[PDB]
Amino acid sequence: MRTHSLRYFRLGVSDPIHGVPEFISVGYVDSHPITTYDSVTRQKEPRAPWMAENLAPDHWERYTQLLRGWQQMFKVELKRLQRHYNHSGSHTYQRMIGCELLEDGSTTGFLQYAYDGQDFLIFNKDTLSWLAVDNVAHTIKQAWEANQHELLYQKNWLEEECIAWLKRFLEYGKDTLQRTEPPLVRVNRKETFPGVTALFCKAHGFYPPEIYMTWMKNEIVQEIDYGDILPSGDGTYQAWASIELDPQSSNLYSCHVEHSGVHMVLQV
Amino acid sequence: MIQRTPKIQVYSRHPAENGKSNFLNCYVSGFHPSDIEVDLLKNGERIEKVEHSDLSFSKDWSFYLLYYTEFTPTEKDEYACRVNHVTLSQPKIVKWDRD
Amino acid sequence: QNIDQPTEMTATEGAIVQINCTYQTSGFNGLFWYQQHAGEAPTFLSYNVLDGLEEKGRFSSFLSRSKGYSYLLLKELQMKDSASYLCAFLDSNYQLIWGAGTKLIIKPDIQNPDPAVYQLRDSKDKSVCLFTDFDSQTNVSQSKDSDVYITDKCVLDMRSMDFKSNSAVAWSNKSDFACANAFN
Amino acid sequence: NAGVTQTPKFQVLKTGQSMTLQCAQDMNHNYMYWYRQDPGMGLRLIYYSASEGTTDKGEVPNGYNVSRSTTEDFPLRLLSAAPSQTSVYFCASSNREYSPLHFGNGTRLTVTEDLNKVFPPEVAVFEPSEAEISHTQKATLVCLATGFYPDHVELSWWVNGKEVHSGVCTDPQPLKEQPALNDSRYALSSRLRVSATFWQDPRNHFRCQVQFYGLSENDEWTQDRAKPVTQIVSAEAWGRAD
Ligand SMILES: *Cc1cccc(C(=O)O)c1O
């Protein structure tokens, strides 16, 4: 097995332009979106069929109402922060909550907030405390730390409920979330400039998106340039790693790739 | 405040070959705030029938999107991605390069 | 699914009572206790979500997640502790599931019991009888006779003399009604 | 803050009448709830609201509707009073979906098929036993409210025209005069225990007040007996050395 993760995001925007929702919420398991809700639709909807097929109407009805509540709270929380900073015009507020289930059976959980896309408040479920970045966040941290019951509720949700939800969704989407599509991996020679040869180790068609790619010699290599792990659009991913051949080296270079418990070596 | 300008990467679902059915991918990521406009371009013309992912969230608080269209590449057809955002005073054109 | 707590408990002033609540669920966002006095609104007493024990004054609240089990412990019982205690838990969907409540009856510590029946002057003209000053272990049974009414045991507090007494009232329009042994 | 204000405290309805229970909180709470409490079962959610602009069915929504136009107000509408709706209704609010509920003081509601079944209490005060005054040096006045329907009464004790609480015990629940009948009229008893001395002072006036909740002065009435309206029915006794 590998790591799996459940994440819920909230975005709030003050004074949004025509059409753009003042509030948006999305859930993800790993890189897949599972749920969505916004201030315009005012409805929690599934973003994956294996969610849609396994969760009764009752679930979408109940969480619809919870999100209507959370939307109102978000609006009030943003308006208050703008008052504290003395900010007019449009600003953003963001929340991320989630857990990881690792293969060894162990877990993590996290909760944080951002103001204009920067870290504002981070939660520690072990010390039951909030890390604040400025005086205005310190202010919010104090109200929250005085409510011992709320901190305990958060710790419980992160450690037990989040993880139970994750294990339930992991079952519902096992065919998508627990499958392997092995990478097709090839090495291209390119004469980057006259008299200078670079090597390109390319992978594509793989899932999950986590992949280790390096160039080794005869011994890791320095001056490795990396492509990002990018979505192919069909639910698979592609990525590459390049090195440049120091002339009159004639050393033995090789591309190493690790994906989903399988190691590959392509020499040239 | 700290605005982040889009990273714009244009590429094909499969290794490209002239005359051979494929998908053209424009992946916009690492931007803030969230309002963004993307058009795929064939020889500078706006392409109609471009599907796209919903707005997506990164743990660093930035956003990412995938814009894609079905296409068959020829030797002479130019393909690009045009992106507008508050960090861009003029839309930014990124051309597709095969290799 | 379910939550269970005892319908009624009875304990003595100054003593200790442990009100148990069991719950079955898949998914849990915590367990609450509310206190509800006769005729009054429930008011929040306790919240447990992690395993263990919270203590505030004479009241403690325990939670075993393992055993699906909570208790509200009241120490040094007072007459004013007489109330319904409402057990409730939040499921995965934040639905609030309520127990049927435990009625807690506190029996006064009557050191000098002086059990009498007395007839009250009928200002203006039924015959009112008063059974008073009896010991808290005495159980006032309602009669059979449908023309003779008998109230439950009431506990009055005369702070005017740091005195506490049990009493029950009986009455009837019957010409043939007698206060002596009306209680029985 | 007042917390949660719920009105009215008491109401009788005829089968088929319409009714609105008011509920308000000044606490900026997102969540408001309507519950019914019936003997031998837990609070049952009628409707709830997660915010101004949204509401949703609880466990027993049938025969009721709500609205949440504002953060403050969550009115509960009884569409067509049925006997099965005889209950005690509590409005509640909470800051969040997981936070503690603040409750209103409740609405005792009785639905009867016939308003001819409504009767105000007869109230009488019984003077203390000479025997008790002698054997205990204490005097136990008894007040008795009888013949009332529905069971919608507040009994208070007044000494010299000011309410008193010390040495008072009122029955928690009214008894039934005819237990067989479901339309049975009710009786309630209360005691006030004072010092024989206090009772012997002829300057001391004792008064039993039962506030009854019944018909409105607006309600139609075609019976000979007085219209059984919301009213205070009172009995009194003066102290005596006698
Ligand atoms: C659907 C859902 C469940 C839990 C938490 C959230 C959130 O927005 O934090 C959401 O959206």
Image: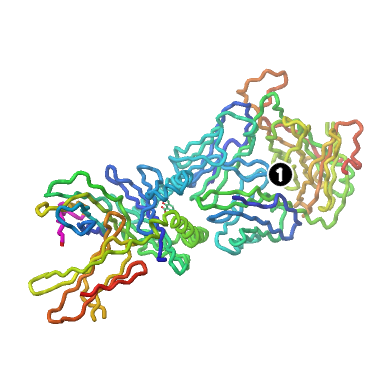
Left or right of A106, for residue A89: left
Q: Position of residue A154 (x, y in %)?
A: 48, 59
Looking at the picture, tell me which residue is in the foreground, C107 or A171.
Answer: A171
Chain identifier of the residue bearing label 1 in the image: D
Left or right of D217, for residue B66: left
Q: Which secondary structure class fits the magenta region best?
A: loop
Would residue C7 be seen by someone viewing this image from the given angle? yes
Which three-letter amino acid code belongs to the residue tagged 1?
A: Val
Residue found 42% across the figure and 45% down from its top: A68
The quadrant of the picture occupied by the C terminus of chain A is bottom left
Left or right of A249, for residue A24: right
Looking at the picture, tell me which residue is in the foreground, A229 or C85.
Answer: A229
Residue D124 placement: quadrant: top right
Q: Position of residue B64 (x, y in %)?
A: 28, 56
Say if C126 sits above or below A222 in the image: above
* Secondary element at image label 1: strand
The quadrant of the picture occupied by the N terminus of chain A is bottom left
Say if D171 sits above or below C57 in the image: above
Q: Position of residue C178 (x, y in %)?
A: 91, 37
Residue C122 placement: quadrant: top right
Q: Position of residue A195 (x, y in %)?
A: 8, 74
Q: Which residue is mark 1?
A: D164
Looking at the picture, tell me which residue is in the foreground, A212 or D181.
Answer: A212
Residue found 35% across the figure and 51% down from its top: A12
Would residue A140 be seen by someone viewing this image from the given angle? no
Dot 1 alpha-carbon crowd within 10 angstroms: few under 14, some 14 to 19, many 20 or more: some
Q: Which residues are magenta?
A: B87-98
Is C58 part of what is drawn in magenta?
A: no
Outermost residue toward the left? A194
Residue found 89% across the figure and 49% down from its top: D135
